[PDB]
Image (cartoon, rainbow over all chains, first blue to last red; front, side):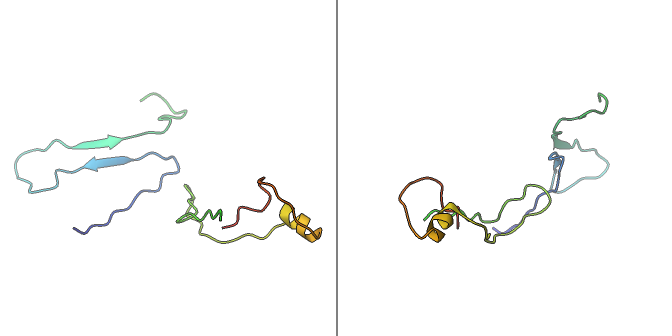
Length: 49
Length: 49
């Protein structure tokens, strides 16, 4: 097994992964697609959503 | 014996700064330039690596 991977830069220190459906992909369908999010302090000041 | 070398200095932030020594004055050095020596276990000599 051989593979390499790397990491983001984030001085906010927050980031997203996306978890693929990494294989064969049909046509004329959909796919539901998921991701994993973090937000250090979220809207630090910002607004709500 | 107390070496402290990290695999890399670990700048969580801008970019990983590497390993190198310093050069400054010391209590050990004060008391050797004094001309002499002592015994303790305090943090006298710098945490050299």
